[PDB]
Image (cartoon, helix red, strand yellow):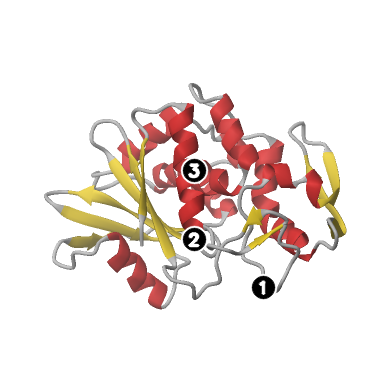
Amino acid sequence: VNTIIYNVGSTTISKYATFLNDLRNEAKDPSLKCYGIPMLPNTNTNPKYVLVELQGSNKKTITLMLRRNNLYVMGYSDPFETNKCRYHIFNDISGTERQDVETTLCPNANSRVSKNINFDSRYPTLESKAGVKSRSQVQLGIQILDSNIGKISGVMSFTEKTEAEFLLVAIQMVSEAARFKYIENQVKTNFNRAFNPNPKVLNLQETWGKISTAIHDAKNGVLPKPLELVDASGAKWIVLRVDEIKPDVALLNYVGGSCQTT
């Protein structure tokens, strides 16, 4: 398992771009792709994970553990207390993947400590914990990310709302940005300020798997069925071809079977 180190406290749009390029290159399968868009690996391709070390201001750091197969954040770790590694596993991680989050994030069995994320990673759950009806009400931003890291990293007790806002911002600026070029570009455009994620960024996030299946299944560039999406203004956006949505996608979710690779 390799880790991508991103200095949140001191960056530029160029360093943000390099970060995402490195994360996509490490997460993606070495050869799997459809219509020239790289795809994530099959669940049993090793390594199954990739770590993202987010270095914030005031020596506050948090490491995210992501599953390569779908880029979902499985949990995170933060340097805690003396010289301990505090790992936090999502409520929706089960079986062997649970000891995996523990041993991958904190390899030293002698100094690791647990602090569960007492709720699952679904957006509606995160939005509920953050006390909002929509994550559109929670602004994203480099400085906002930095601030949320500092509210969690090394801090013994923190509220679920605090944790949820950190998770909402980090997932979207890391996982969602890696998957979608559009989302990366939204962050780059508002790099020095806070911004509310638009209807297109949220839709893309919610239709990623659908988009990925449609592209994998697309015959001669034509999507199996018209795919209804929504643009930046919130208008219904019906896509019929791969060429119409491909500019927004950086990585495709894993979809079994052969496809038009170029």
On the question of residue 100 being in view, the answer is: yes
Query: How dense is the environment of label 2, judged by Cα within 10 Å: few (below 14), some, or many (20 and up)?
Result: some
Q: In the displayed structure, would residue 169 be above or below residue 30?
A: above
- Label placed on residue 120: 2
Dot 1: what SS? loop
* First reached walking from the N terminus: tag 1 or tag 2: 2
In the rendered image, residue 28, in percent from the top left (x then y), is placed at 53, 58
Dot 2: what SS? loop
Q: In the displayed structure, would residue 136 be above or below residue 220?
A: above
Question: Is the C-beta separation of discs 3 and 1 under 8 Å?
Answer: no
Q: CA distance from mark 2 to mark 3?
A: 25 Å
* First reached walking from the N terminus: tag 2 or tag 3: 3
* Picture quadrant where residue 29 is located: bottom right
Q: Is residue 228 left or right of residue 111?
A: right
Dot 3: what SS? helix
Q: Which residue is mark 3?
A: 20
Indicate the amino acid at tag 1.
Gly
Residue at the location (66% across, 47% down)? 249
* Picture quadrant where residue 47 is located: bottom left
Q: Which residue is mark 1?
A: 256
Query: How dense is the environment of label 1, judged by Cα within 10 Å: few (below 14), some, or many (20 and up)?
Result: few
For the N terminus, the quadrant is bottom left
Q: In the displayed structure, would residue 134 be above or below residue 94?
A: above
- Compare residues 17 and 211 and report the one nearer the observer: 17
Q: CA distance from mark 1 to mark 2?
A: 26 Å
On the question of residue 72 being in view, the answer is: no
* First reached walking from the N terminus: tag 3 or tag 1: 3
Residue at the location (48% across, 72% down)? 45
User: Which residue is farthest left?
Assistant: 82
- Compare residues 121 and 188 and report the one nearer the observer: 188
For the C terminus, the quadrant is bottom right
* Picture quadrant where residue 61 is located: top left
